[PDB]
Structures are given as C-alpha cells and as structure tokens.
Length: 50
Length: 48
Ligand SMILES: *[C@@H]1O[C@H](CO)[C@@H](O)[C@H](O)[C@H]1NC(C)=O
Image (cartoon, rainbow over all chains, first blue to last red; front, top):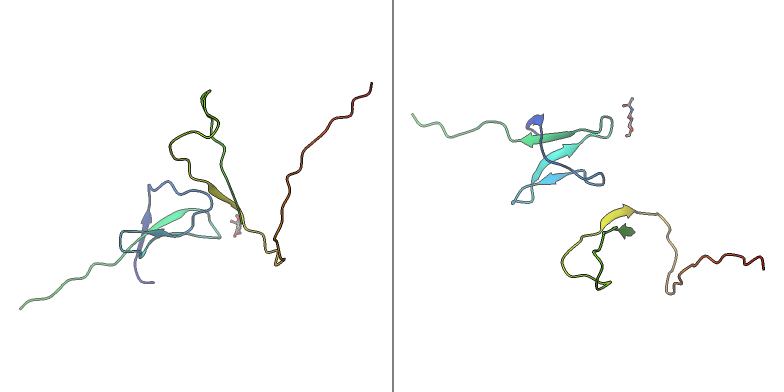
C-alpha cells in the first residue's frame, strides 16, 4: 500500500492485527517484527484547477 | 477455533443479561472430523 504510517492511540486487542474504518479499508497495521500499531493514512491528494 | 471469556457475574441468575463478547483464544490446525464431544471433570481420591 501507499500511505503515511503514524503513531496510533487505538487500543488493539492482542489477537487483532489489521484495522478498518467505516469503508472496510485498511486503516492500521500491526507489524510482526515489532509489535506496534501503525495507523495508515492515504497520502495528500486533490484536484488542481487552473 | 476456541473462543473464550471470563466474566465476573454478581450473585444472581447464572446466565446473566447483557453482552460479553468472547475473544478468539486459539486457532489449532487440526484437520480431523469432529461429530461428538464430552466434558472432562476432575475427581479427588477419598483416602478413607
Ligand atoms: C521477531 O518477530 C517475532 C514475531 O514475529 C517477535 O516476537 C520478535 O520480537 C522479533 N524479534 C525482534 C528482535 O524484535
């Protein structure tokens, strides 16, 4: 995926890995190597009007 | 798949009201046919 990985304040349960929003799209990930939760936010984008 | 939960129930009806969701405890890669089950109890020797 392409996104920004940030610190999270979401209290994940030990079994829980992925995280999802109301759109059932990946919003957080738990890394196997280091057991920490990285919030995933899509990178900034927008329409350009001239 | 085994799911479990421990809930402190205030003295009353054994099956209480309300919700207490069971968290996933273990997923075991067994691959066997299971149609029947039985509960195991512990019994103490009397020594009398
Ligand atoms: C390697 O990964 C395991 C789980 O994937 C983790 O428990 C362990 O801490 C990792 N090793 C190090 C040095 O972080």
